[PDB]
Image (tube, rainbow, N blue to C red):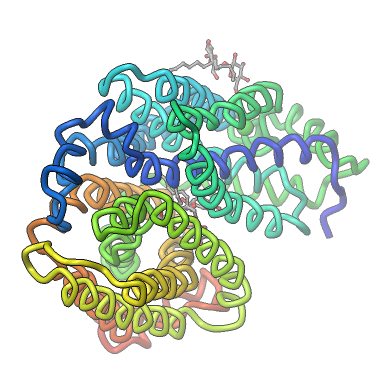
Length: 485
Ligand SMILES: CCCCCCC(CCCCCC)(CO[C@H]1O[C@@H](CO)[C@H](O)[C@@H](O)[C@@H]1O)CO[C@H]1O[C@@H](CO)[C@H](O)[C@@H](O)[C@@H]1O
Ligand SMILES: CCCCCCC(CCCCCC)(CO[C@H]1O[C@@H](CO)[C@H](O)[C@@H](O)[C@@H]1O)CO[C@H]1O[C@@H](CO)[C@H](O)[C@@H](O)[C@@H]1O
Ligand SMILES: OC[C@H]1O[C@@H](O)[C@H](O)[C@@H](O)[C@@H]1O
Ligand SMILES: [Cl-]
């Protein structure tokens, strides 16, 4: 019943949001392919590529175990973790669009720092800057886009952002496959192409307006409704406008969500706002996402085949994220948590044992065409199972079970421990693979068993139930009944 359709304002916001999502996915998916390139390894980590062919030909589990090489991947997420708090502050004091702008600018400057890197300190300075971009943009871009979108197609545009991210992953994989055949400086093109959507984002981010919600929260109702009318193209926006003032009056009268978050009425949610992210990262999904090319390279794929296999993981992640829309709205959260968990579990066991039967505990041995094919196939079945379970639900259900009196705290801790464990995966996958050998896949498998047991016994169905009623579904539960008075 909100009047107002598609305007040039929402086209602009959608250009900027698409650029931001593509940037997320691209900077996530480019690092692994570039780490697998022997030009890049020669120029920044020579001690690593010496230990791979003539010297140390078969030592599969530890060829790439170097803390600086993995810092190249992880520093982005370290910086994103810290920059999310900084973006919280700057969105409050100045505005969400300012954080959008700062994130786009960080994307641009860091992409250029990466492309022009003549030493390793430049390299991870650029990565830290891309992380600053992620920290400022993941905050600002989605809720700016949702505020700007007409209520009718709002969900469609948010789903568009969501899949902009995964298609960006696939785009980065493809760019890596392509630039790897450049005779020189292909990794530069790979890391640097991020600068194009980054400057589209910088420009659009600068010219776009403060949202009517923002003007309402800083007391400019007069400007707010005029801007709402101009952004909607409808000649009266009263129904939407006073729902916005209701929302901002409600948000204003909550004192502090951090003291409410740890009162017992909300401690199921708090538990799940801490357990869901950890679990999502201890699945081992970013093993694949960050390090699929170098994993295939340690097992003896060959550069070309490793990059192509990363491309197929990207294709499967994209298609399965497509079906995850239909999946999360046809089936319940418990069903898909359980199904995806057992799928990932079977695949992790199988992959770990193929690798163990070919290389043992000493890292010496040969892959076979059939075992290489099976390892890739079950990696992909694994990421497909993740892509319609712990992937989307790992953000969906923490927001779902969080009333507005607790939602800022809930999403703060959600994103921060998710980012911290993302960082740990990126910083320690290769050294864990060295110390645990093929047993690391068994470790990830047993932790997925643990998290699925956790979901089966502790999280009740939250699909289709309203926020104001989650309380009841929480004390119908045999265990959480302990916490609601
Ligand atoms: C800590 C790091 C630096 C922060 C700089 C913030 C930036 C420029 C951002 C870049 C330009 C925009 C992409 C926002 O500047 C603009 O922000 C707009 C909100 O979006 C306001 O509508 C506008 O009035 C303001 O000038 C300038 O700060 C201003 O913030 C105002 C309060 O927001 C202050 O009243 C003002 O003393 C201050 O000088
Ligand atoms: C380098 C980032 C890679 C992706 C990481 C997950 C990420 C991106 C930001 C992560 C936080 C960074 C500090 C994509 O979001 C999800 O989109 C789903 C769509 O089906 C996918 O299935 C799922 O795998 C993916 O995690 C989560 O989305 C963020 O932005 C909003 C989107 O609208 C969400 O409203 C918000 O709360 C969430 O914070
Ligand atoms: O597709 C891979 C991505 O899936 C998302 O659900 C996770 O939040 C990210 O950490 C991961 O990189
Ligand atoms: Cl704004």
